[PDB]
Amino acid sequence: MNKEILAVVEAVSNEKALPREKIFEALESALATATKKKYEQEIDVRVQIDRKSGDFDTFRRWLVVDEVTQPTKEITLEAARYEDESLNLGDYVEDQIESVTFDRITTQTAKQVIVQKVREAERAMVVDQFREHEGEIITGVVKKVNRDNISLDLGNNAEAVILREDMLPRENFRPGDRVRGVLYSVRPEARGAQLFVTRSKPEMLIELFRIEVPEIGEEVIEIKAAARDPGSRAKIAVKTNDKRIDPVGACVGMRGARVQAVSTELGGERIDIVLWDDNPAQFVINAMAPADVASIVVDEDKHTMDIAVEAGNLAQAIGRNGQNVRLASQLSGWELNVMTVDDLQAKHQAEAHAAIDTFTKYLDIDEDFATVLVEEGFSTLEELAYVPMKELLEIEGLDEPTVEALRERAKNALATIAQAQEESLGDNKPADDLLNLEGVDRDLAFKLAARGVCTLEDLAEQGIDDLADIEGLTDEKAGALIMAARNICWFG
Amino acid sequence: VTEFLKPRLVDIEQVSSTHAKVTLEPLERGFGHTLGNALRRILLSSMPGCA
Amino acid sequence: ATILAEQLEAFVPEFDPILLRPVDDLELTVRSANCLKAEAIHYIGDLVQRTEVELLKTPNLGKKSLTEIKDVLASRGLSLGMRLENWPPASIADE
Amino acid sequence: RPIGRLLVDACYSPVERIAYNVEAARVEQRTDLDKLVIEMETNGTIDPEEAIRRA
């Protein structure tokens, strides 16, 4: 009876490595809840278990509050202090109440609350101790297969889930099968599956390589990037600081044994291992393997790279359904355009001709001088307007007066282009002039400007009949806007 | 107390041509007969026309 | 249906009146009612102006009787410490 | 809800016997007109014109 409480507390404390205090607090809450259910009225109840005897006293708790909303469970601070002057806001006032007999009903409630406390203590501490597993490749047994997810048993009442998107496209699991996967997220669904496991994401590939390649687990080789088409093909980029170690050779292993072990665990996924380079162009050449790259052109402003390949290698460089270029682009972070050497030259000739036409049209220069600007690397009016004067003065035949005139023309061309578009639609010119009339939304200003009504004066000159075809403009609203425009233009 | 089950023609299954079949629900435990009888007696004669 | 329907168209600021009630109408325990009468609280409008801290100073008013008064006032949508401007109305000052 | 209530059945129905007798009409010079004479049988809780109006 008495000594049995101590023996139970000691057995549970030792078996679940849990603080005795946390078990008692929970038993007190369990007994309070079991007591509340025996009364027809909603009462507040505190239970206190004596830590030496295992005896327990049950109260009618009265949550000491400032304002009473529930007179059956709450008492004012003034009324609580009339019974005991030591009470504060948030304390409990008690009332001698018959403790519930410990029948198999309370026993079952106590068992359930202990089990729940162990899930939030023993199992929580087990998950904390398995900080590596929360991130590394956990191993589970398939408990249940549904259409949209697989429930894994990890042991110790821990359940994990693999979602349909987190599976490989050709995997078929049965109840009782062993499955490995990366624990990529821990949420708070204690009842059910709080653990989310992936086999499809790139982290599964990284951690399989960490286990299979000791040199990655020892931090001698680093995986810098991983790009993956799950169950089909992946690319990994590897670097080492030790010049004595070939990082690609280490990840492949003797006759490919290491990469084949990882591929086999991923259902026969093809894995390319590439050397990481700190030069983006050299890294993209490595990422494009097994296709040979002839030339690369880098557009830093668009964050894009044009990759020229021999006409025989084009199909290999793109890969089946663009898989090779897509995985290389995801691995590099660059947008990758794969074309032939002939197509790259034709593209550059078309861009050079478009730049020459743009410069000839807007800068009032001859085609010979526009060609020199494009040969010196200028492709946009913005570059010519904003580039440091020193770079323009390095061009053979440019003097300081001609560079100043060229920049002034480029700025005036940029200004004119902006103003023209802003007046054609409703970007700025018609979004201020035509939209001056109270009531003009940006859409209506662009609809007006599409009819050639670009200014508040142009609107003041219109009839209702001239605007009657504008979708969303009633004759009354047209008349009001024309009168508002006339009031500002002719009577302001 | 004056609130009844206001009915409606849930479907008009007009079978073929010059022939319909109009079903009305729901009525009270006794109003199907009084509306069927009222509409039956009025359509039979009251309804005018030329021949 | 049109014929049959045409053949039938010749046939077819001190709260409110609750504040003016005596405290005895609140169904309080004989203890709570006698404690309120000893402090000259006759109407519900007088009771609603008193704070919980003031009622606890009343001789023989316990924490239990204060909880009863709150639960009963709450059942009528009233709370302790409401300020009524112009209470008592001149209609009550002559009894 | 307590044990002291007693529930009787509820016959919420004021009328007892409704008998119509159609008959020929002569007030109007036009013939082939009819008169509808409805003798109801109320228990006193419903006015007859109110009954025919609600019907």
Image (cartoon, helix red, strand yellow):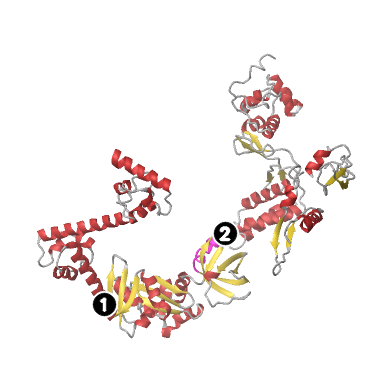
The span from disc 1 to disc 2 (Cα, nearest Å) is 64 Å
Q: Which residue is mark 1?
A: A346
Which of the chains bears the disc numbered 1?
Answer: A
The residue at the point 77 percent across, 48 percent down is A101
Q: Looking at the image, which residue sits at the far top?
A: C94
Three-letter amino acid code at the position of disc 2:
Ala
Residue A123 locus on image (x, y percent): 59, 61
User: What range is drawn magenta here?
Assistant: A125-136
**Nearest the camera: A111 or C13?**
C13
Residue D26 locus on image (x, y percent): 85, 43
The residue at the point 66 percent across, 15 percent down is C93
**Where C1 sits versus A60, above or below?**
below
Three-letter amino acid code at the position of disc 1:
Ala
Residue B33 locus on image (x, y percent): 81, 56
Is residue C17 visible to the viewer in this orientation of the structure? yes
Q: Label 1's element?
A: helix
**Where A48 sits versus A11, above or below?**
above
Is residue A492 visible to the viewer in this orientation of the structure? no
Q: Nearer the viewer, mark 1 or mark 2?
A: 1
Q: Residues within 10 Å of mark 1 (few under 14, many from 20)?
A: few
**Nearest the camera: C41 or D4?**
D4
Which of the chains bears the disc numbered 2?
Answer: A
Picture disc at residue A256:
none
Q: Label 2's element?
A: helix
Picture disc at residue A124:
2
Q: Split into 4 quadrants, where in the image is the C terminus of chain A?
A: top left
